[PDB]
Amino acid sequence: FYTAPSTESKFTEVLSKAKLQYPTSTTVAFADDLLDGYAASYFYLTSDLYMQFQVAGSSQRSELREMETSGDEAAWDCTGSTAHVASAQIAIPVQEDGIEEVTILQVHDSDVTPVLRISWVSSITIDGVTSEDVVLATIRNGIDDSTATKTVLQAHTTSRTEFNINVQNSKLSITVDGTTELDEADISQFDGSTCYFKAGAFNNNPTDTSANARIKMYELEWVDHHH
Ligand SMILES: O=C(O)[C@H]1O[C@@H](O[C@H]2[C@H](O)[C@H](O)[C@H](O[C@H]3[C@H](O)[C@H](O)[C@H](O[C@H]4[C@H](O)[C@H](O)[C@H](O[C@H]5[C@H](O)[C@H](O)[C@H](O)O[C@@H]5C(=O)O)O[C@@H]4C(=O)O)O[C@@H]3C(=O)O)O[C@@H]2C(=O)O)[C@@H](O)[C@@H](O)[C@@H]1O
Image (cartoon, rainbow, N blue to C red):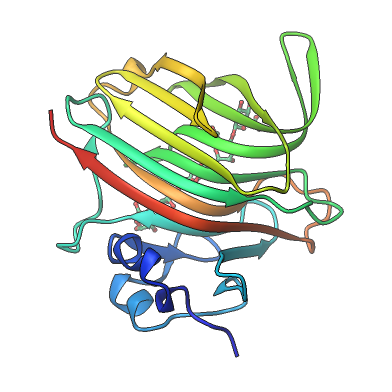
């Protein structure tokens, strides 16, 4: 009894350029399935026209993964000359009790390393400064280094917020409601990797493994701009 995100033309292009993974990394719906009206409790259109992702459990996800229209997985040069841009209007609801971090947008390499995660966090401490109820950027320092550089981007609001990720040459920038909050962070540690975008809800380290993480997107797109 769920309405499909494909019923809204604002999502046609991104769905044509995506596959949906749930609840782990296995694809449940390819682009053709998504365009044919795929809908489930974990991926549906709300009455006010948001594409909503919902998932329970540690490190589980309901996430779109960037694809080419040819059916090839997106695998662009992480630090190449072509700009790659992901834009999303996201409303992050107050999360259920026991949900502690939800990743909403990623730049991921073609193996096992997230270049960037944008996530909501109940709390975070960075260089001795603790922030609560914020949206955070996490950039991994290397494939062989589990540590990351973390940057608070925004105090959490339930209001629809524009997020824009721009990746070009060895630099990555993030704008939030038009304001640059991460200005040309270095990602040269991914030279010689390939990359793709992801968007949705990816539930990180919950304290209640039965609680549902929930993220809503009013607009979503990923594009290339050729130098
Ligand atoms: O807690 C700490 O100590 C540190 O945590 C750091 O952040 C963590 C996060 O908390 C998450 O755990 C995050 O999880 C990553 C995970 O490390 C892997 O990168 C994994 O990669 C999957 C891909 O997203 C993708 O879904 C892929 O799909 C493939 C798959 O092969 C599929 O079967 C099919 O064949 O093809 C598809 C495809 O489309 O390419 O599968 C990958 C997989 O192996 O599961 O996904 C998550 C993720 O980010 O999505 O990891 C970070 C981390 O950096 O380790 C950080 O906060 C740090 O500061 C802390 O100290």
